[PDB]
Amino acid sequence: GVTTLLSYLASESEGSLKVQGWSASGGRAEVVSDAEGTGGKAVKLTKEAGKSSWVLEYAAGNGAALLQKGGQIRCRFKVSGALAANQYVMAFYWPVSSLPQGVALTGDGGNNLLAAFYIQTDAKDLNVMYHNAKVATNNLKLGTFGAFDNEWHTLAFRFAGNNSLQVTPVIDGQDGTPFTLTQSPVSAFAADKLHVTDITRGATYPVLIDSIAVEVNS
């Protein structure tokens, strides 16, 4: 089976991010009961609007083995609150300090990230987007969970191995359209860490996290 590069589970170690090796800043992380969370648990992430965006970080390395062997970046989450057009849930950024020899991302933007994916509603749907353009009107829409709701969802990004940069998003257990990683303008996040954040100081949706993981094929 797979090996775990990193994980957070709300059902492990009383849901403690700290015990599980993550660094957390901004906002509040409250371990809560949710009957459809794994083990009946989740972590609820909020902040005071206008105050700092929350950020969770894990020391993920440069991901070379993920690229070589394939694997997945995954999260199970539930969004809380009323549908509000254009409002963010969260983003996943994984800048890397190098790519393997002979691997190079196409495009301009000048930064190498294995993840630059964010979750946002339009006026009707919950969308998964790729922050790979200078202006967001040109960011790629990777797929949608459909009409916005407050149910649990799963999201994964599957890497095929052999150093392929062609990733398949997996939305509620079903593949979406494959896409190829490119350079990205995202530059503000420390290299070789996975950063999970609600992006903005402005109001964002409260979110419940069941798990976050990166797994590498064995």
Image (cartoon, grey):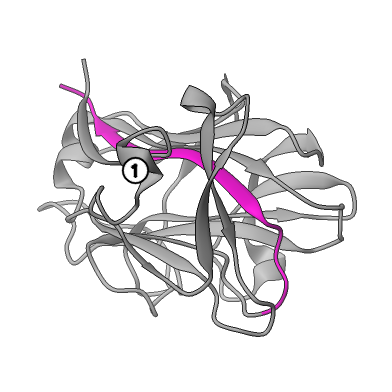
Question: Which sits in the foreground, 183 or 190?
Answer: 190
43 displayed left or right of 25: right
Q: Would you say residue 212 is visible in this rendering?
A: yes
The reply to whether the magenta stretch includes residue 177 is no
Query: What is the x, y in percent for residue 1?
Result: 21, 15
Please name the residue shown 49% across and 25% down the image. Answer: 38
Query: What is the x, y in percent for residue 82?
Result: 86, 53
Query: What is the x, y in percent for residue 112?
Result: 31, 64
Q: Would you say residue 8 is visible in this rendering?
A: no
Q: Which residues are magenta?
A: 202-218
Residue type beneath disc 1:
Leu
173 displayed left or right of 82: left
In the displayed orientation, state which residue is furthest to the right. 123
Question: Which sits in the foreground, 168 or 146?
Answer: 146
Name the residue tied to disc 1.
Answer: 165
Question: Which sits in the foreground, 150 or 133?
Answer: 150
Query: What is the x, y in percent for residue 202?
Result: 70, 78
Question: Which sits in the foreground, 101 or 62?
Answer: 62
The reply to whether the magenta stretch includes residue 214 is yes
